Image (cartoon, rainbow over all chains, first blue to last red; front, top):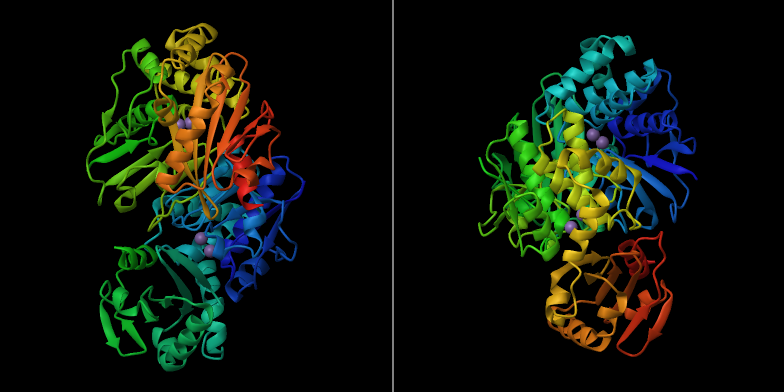
Length: 308
Length: 308
Ligand SMILES: [Mn+2]
Ligand SMILES: [Mn+2]
Ligand SMILES: [Mn+2]
Ligand SMILES: [Mn+2]
């Protein structure tokens, strides 16, 4: 029996790391057929982490999952998952996100916790079972936590994430702030990249009531680096929205040095979500928010605007 | 800060017990606004357990859950939950079932394990946390486990359910086989009850792909006690299917002594699910299975038939 372990499409550092980490967990637990996979490209940020701790990228999933045992990490929504996910047998989910568009035939292990990072939950699982946390594995856990939490500044970050990171740094042999900022910087180069690349780099679809929304995330050293390409961005966001039948396309731009975030929003349901945010720039194509609240989570806020 | 804790509509013993057990857990955890509720009638089986351990029945939920904190036990599918569940904020789910028709705006705690009973999971939460298990609480846990497992003979039963029961017996101060058989017998009187009563006693709706299916469970001393009323059963099942627009209505009849089960199946997708079982008799309106495979679970097998 093989078991396929993977994170979401357009994987982020958490998605790649958690797949490798959970494959380790399964193997230490005695499940030798467990194997990590990815559903997309390894980003520059994630490559920095993999290179630092000398871990190879997981294999790109090309197998049909029909009748196969599957473990999902860092996602549950089927449209974020493998093309053949609906034909798989999902044994286990480990995740830190909202639940939607998820259905199984029978019972399964499902573990979600409202923490800042999937690797934090996996850290706790290793702990609970008393399994070895190798230095590389600790490095990937720490990388994931720094990535998802943005060096502990995102509204999703919790003290469990901070505590896990503090306990992992000596195992990984790494200074959190120094390594962390280097890692974040390694995925923050935008000006020489195409609009198509930026909008697909870290981008996921969401099932929100009757609607399907696309959300892309871009890190930069300066918000304006990205945001004065607004016109070209909007154009591509509208084109993709039509081609994929999205009801909404949100671009979240985040300053890694500053921790400030803004959103650029396009699509059929644009005006409805605009009411939920501080609109600073608007037109027929799009709206641009002022710098977003540090404490409120964006995904739930958008969901509530579309459903409520 | 209220938090409503409840099980599914037409609650079984697991659904009633687990709500009370989880309310205790929350109070014990420090959450003082936590309260147990029920969404329907207390069955004869459940009443026997409540009387044995002097636990009153939880309050019938009548409040609108709009904007309220909720914890679900022993279910997740929205059609099985409160009428206002979509307007609530689901903080926590503890369950042992398939997942479907479940969506949240934001992150949450979700704990599902593929075990025989929700109370088994709640028991593990007490053990993990080092919480004291009162003898009344231990009795409810044990009752739920005996109920869902049918005195440890159902396909869903695991060694974790057995282990937990062995340790709970001395806390509850009860003989498992003796109390268990009494409890099961108390909910197994069928010939005196109307067809309408039997089909609404332990009946839940399910989201299975494009379909909505209704499944009713009936415990009996002897399978033929119920199944000799075949035609009266079918008639009410078709009537309800038409009136509620179900694609399928399954009646599972289980012998409490030997744990043999048979299914009586009616509705639009009847032929499609008949494919997945050993059909002992059939006509235009219904099929009746032979004694169902002792290892494989019924709900997943139905779901699989309606999809693949
Ligand atoms: Mn991710
Ligand atoms: Mn993540
Ligand atoms: Mn139940
Ligand atoms: Mn149950």
